[PDB]
Length: 399
Ligand SMILES: *[C@@H]1O[C@H](CO)[C@@H](O[C@@H]2O[C@H](CO)[C@@H](O)[C@H](O)[C@H]2NC(C)=O)[C@H](O)[C@H]1NC(C)=O
Ligand SMILES: *[C@@H]1O[C@H](CO)[C@@H](O[C@@H]2O[C@H](CO)[C@@H](O)[C@H](O)[C@H]2NC(C)=O)[C@H](O)[C@H]1NC(C)=O
Ligand SMILES: *[C@@H]1O[C@H](CO)[C@@H](O[C@@H]2O[C@H](CO)[C@@H](O)[C@H](O)[C@H]2NC(C)=O)[C@H](O)[C@H]1NC(C)=O
Ligand SMILES: *[C@@H]1O[C@H](CO)[C@@H](O)[C@H](O)[C@H]1NC(C)=O
Ligand SMILES: [Ca+2]
Image (tube, rainbow, N blue to C red; front, top):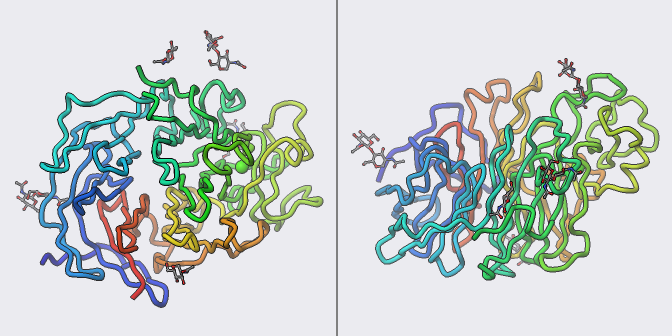
């Protein structure tokens, strides 16, 4: 019904994939989720939670017919989730995770129903607070929280609550203190993207790793350290959960080329930071810290991860590099997963990310490129995603 077009060289779809721009003019759209009524809720950062009414003509033929601001709150900056029954919306500021009653008869939120479920999350620099509600354990809410600086010493202290993911049984609800949740992982500089694999309920996160990396004082920031895919075990069990994934004393290797003191290190292995606390060595990184399951190209900046219904594929948004001479990212990629809920690629792979939508000319980014942020599936397996810098929502599907 509406003719919406991109204002930059359009994304390139891999063979077998098609897409359509369905919404424009949003302020800075981040997390997105469908409600029970087929409306798309958008966390529009600096505005609040917006609901988009869609007409669906099938395939990529969707049009926005109306938009409404459900929750007006300029402090909401990224995180959004909705209960499986559709009656509770969760959204986060830098400091607080709020729960609101959502009236799906009227598609309204009464602001007086707001309650704080998690608090004390405030810190500088990395200010997003991703929310994930478990499907396998529907009363479990995961909350991710990044570092206070590029290299944050408080991330060494687990009680600070910096650079870690926590889980809360919201059925047991004054709000939880952040560090009162179950520890899913710490030493996670800024793992904005957190998802659950339906094959087995495995918890996965994607990492925005350190900027300005040095190795024996040599600048190796152009191609290191890699971005990471981290595994946190099964929700409710302790196996492969609650460890320290290395920030800020250990980083993962992406590019071996010209890397000082490589030794026995391979792609995917973690090595000690030049600025690691006194006494930490490469060996400490091997024995005491948890390595990533897979690494990606340095600085692609992943922001969300969503699995399809079968659990055969995860989709990841690469929001794009900001400080690399030639830009990288600005894409949507897929990673293949096996029957045991783990990636089919080995941990030393440099080719695990398969291109779904890419920018045609990375030299133009980020000014003339989309910057994917949030993903969500609808009930029939179409993928929807936000581009915050461009104020856009897209639909994506196999043709
Ligand atoms: C949401 O709906 C409002 C109201 O229809 C839209 O605001 C209009 O935007 C158009 C340009 O697209 C203007 O020409 C109109 O004057 C605006 N109307 C009003 C009353 O403000 C808004 O653009 C829509 N936004 C989204 C994201 O759908
Ligand atoms: C790690 O972080 C925790 C955060 O709780 C620090 O504990 C606080 O320390 C400040 C300053 O010493 C005190 O004013 C608070 O009373 C402490 N809070 C608690 C819960 O006791 C701790 O000092 C930091 N250092 C560590 C523990 O290594
Ligand atoms: C280790 O910490 C030092 C902190 O000094 C970092 O070195 C800084 O790197 C930038 C280059 O991007 C220089 O402009 C600064 O001048 C350097 N030191 C300062 C601020 O005086 C180094 O990047 C860190 N190495 C990492 C993160 O691997
Ligand atoms: C948040 O931290 C303060 C200490 O700074 C603590 O007293 C409070 O209990 C924490 N949050 C809640 C609501 O427990
Ligand atoms: Ca790590």
